[PDB]
Every structure is written in structure tokens, then in C-alpha cells.
Image (cartoon, rainbow, N blue to C red):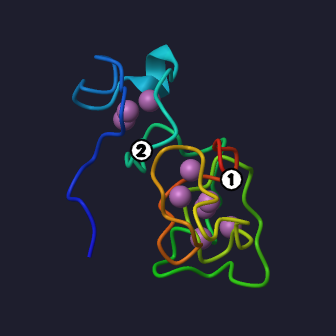
Amino acid sequence: GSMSSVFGAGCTDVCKQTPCGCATSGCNCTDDCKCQSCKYGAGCTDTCKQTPCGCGSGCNCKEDCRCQSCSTACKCAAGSCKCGKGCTGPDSCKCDRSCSCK
Ligand SMILES: [Cd+2]
Ligand SMILES: [Cd+2]
Ligand SMILES: [Cd+2]
Ligand SMILES: [Cd+2]
Ligand SMILES: [Cd+2]
Ligand SMILES: [Cd+2]
Ligand SMILES: [Cd+2]
Ligand SMILES: [Cd+2]
Ligand SMILES: [Cd+2]
């Protein structure tokens, strides 16, 4: 129940590479980047990618995490998701822990 995208809202051509070059040439993408490959390392942990997630109440991520399973519930509610997504809730949120809302 989500958009089938591997990109965010402003990815570089380096992200459009193959393999993804952001892990070689640096990352410069947006907070919506659904690319588990470039933003990894400085955002996640080996406990998050376990699928669904092994973090839960025992997280070991960085901060650039886009998962709402281990990240704490946003204060988004009643139109309080100013990033522009407008999820207004952690369950609807698909942003990261350092986004505009959070
Ligand atoms: Cd990207
Ligand atoms: Cd990428
Ligand atoms: Cd990137
Ligand atoms: Cd994570
Ligand atoms: Cd997680
Ligand atoms: Cd985590
Ligand atoms: Cd949020
Ligand atoms: Cd959101
Ligand atoms: Cd957001």
C-alpha cells in the first residue's frame, strides 16, 4: 500500500547510476529517497534490514532511517506533517528521522 518508487523527490543522476554511485561518489538526494542502497550505512543498521525489522524497541540505527517500525512516533497528527507529505501519523509516514516533520 504505497508508491512503487526507488527514488525520492530529487535524486541525483549519481543515484540513477547502476550500480548506485552514491556509495562511490557521495549522496545528495532528498528525504524521500526510497533507495535502501545509497543512504545506507549512515542511516540504518544491520538490525533494521532484517525484514520486517529486528530493531523494534531495541534499535541500533544511525539517524537517516526511513522506517517507522523502529523510529519513534512522529508528532504528526491533525495536519501536523509540514514536510509536504501530509501523512499526519507514523503509520502513514514514509519519511526519515531527520525529515522536515521529524
Ligand atoms: Cd536518490
Ligand atoms: Cd540511490
Ligand atoms: Cd543518494
Ligand atoms: Cd533503519
Ligand atoms: Cd527499522
Ligand atoms: Cd533501527
Ligand atoms: Cd512524520
Ligand atoms: Cd510523513
Ligand atoms: Cd516528513
What is the number of callouts on the image? 2
Q: Nearer the viewer, residue 45 or 99?
A: 99
Residue drawn at x 74%, y 51% is 62
> According to the image, label 1 marks what residue?
97
Which residue is farthest front? 78
To which residue does mark 2 refer?
37
Which kind of residue does numbered mark 1 sit on? Arg
Picture residue at 64% right of the left edge, 59% below the top: 80
| Nearest to the observer: residue 32 or residue 84 | 84
Using the image, determine if residue 9 lies above or below residue 95: above
Badge 2 amino acid: Ser
Q: Nearer the viewer, mark 2 or mark 1?
A: 1
Q: CA distance from mark 2 to mark 1?
A: 17 Å
| The N terminus, quarter of image | bottom left
Seen at 52% across and 39% down, the residue is: 31
Asked if 84 appears above or below 28 in the picture, the reply is: below
For this view, does 102 lie left or right of residue 66?
right
Label 2, residues with CA under 10 Å away: few <14, some 14-19, many ≥20:
some
Mark 2 within 8 Å of ligand 2, using the beta carbon: yes
